[PDB]
Amino acid sequence: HHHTMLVYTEEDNISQLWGLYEMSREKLENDDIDASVSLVFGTIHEADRILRNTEDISTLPKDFHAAYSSALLAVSELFEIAQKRLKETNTEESYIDAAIERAQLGLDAPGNESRLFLALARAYLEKVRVLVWRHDNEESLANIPVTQLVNPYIEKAIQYLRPLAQDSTEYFDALTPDSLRPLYILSSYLFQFGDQFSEAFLLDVCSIITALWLKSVVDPNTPAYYKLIAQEAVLNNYTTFAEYYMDLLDNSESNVDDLINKASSWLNNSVDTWNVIYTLDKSPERLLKLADIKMDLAQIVQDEASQDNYLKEACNAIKEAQGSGVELSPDYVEFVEAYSA
């Protein structure tokens, strides 16, 4: 039924305001959730004071509405726990809604837009995840086509993401491998409902995503932990695109020798990014996914000399993976056995 406050002046407390949110996320990483919720709620209550107490609101910067938005969204993320402090009436989706609303308000406000855009595209994508769930379990929506439903939101998310991917928008603190997690929602959405989007479109977006993940980990000294979080994502992206081409390659309505040539380069982009991950984390169980790509590569390459070669590498990958104490699942064991025959 109350809230105490920690600040002193305006220009440097829109800055204070972010530190508070940032701390929310740092407390999250150490698994301390309640602390995070307390920081998140703090941030909200504090932005409220900042609101009432300023002389003109239209003065307040884009970067403020972003912080405020990004804090509201954090409640929907930790709603499981945070709901225990709220009236018996609020909901995860209402906060995603709030986050969207407050973010949008800053569109007019003056200031750098980088933070506010990320704040939007995040809230939007999060509304898409929830919307998809509602389509499946709410019966009001059981017959509204899920594309019809979530598209308007995907469209908006892409809209603010595109600017950020551009090299013109240079790096900023709040573009972190974590801040980008919602991008996972955009990926698996293009995955299900892809047979509805032009290959050019699919390519435009699935490159905006790739671009962003890498850019969040640009600074050469990003701790290796974070570099991993992002490279994994880029890998997941590259492989998913290669598996896209491989899927219609066997269908072959177009019968083009071209699109085997297209998928190939996507899988070397996966082998590349893999070695980057294997470098920041040399765990030997990873070898199985290097095997996985090799096999996917032999399954399309033209000439038998190369197929035979790719397989000989995936075979060695799994042998070594086991030679270092990984317990091979059945699939892998009856591959190693099958090749050496």
Image (cartoon, helix red, strand yellow):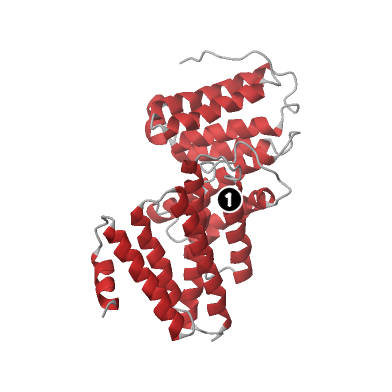
Q: State whether residue 193 appears in this view.
A: no
Residue 171 vertical placement versus 277 (above, below) = above
Instruction: Give the number of callouts.
Output: 1
Q: Nearer the viewer, residue 240 or 132?
A: 240
Q: Quadrant of the C terminus?
A: bottom left
Question: How far across and down, in percent of the image, does residue 177 sit?
Answer: 53, 44
Q: Nearer the viewer, residue 55 or 32?
A: 32
Q: Nearer the viewer, residue 210 or 93?
A: 210
Q: Amino acid at mark 1?
A: Leu
Q: Secondary structure at mark 1?
A: helix
Question: How far across and down, in percent of the image, does residue 6 sit?
Answer: 57, 14
Q: Quadrant of the N terminus?
A: top left
Question: How far across and down, in percent of the image, does residue 261 sit?
Answer: 56, 78
User: Which residue shows up at 63% across the image and 35% down it?
Assistant: 66
Q: Which residue is mark 1?
A: 214
Q: Nearer the viewer, residue 45 or 233?
A: 233
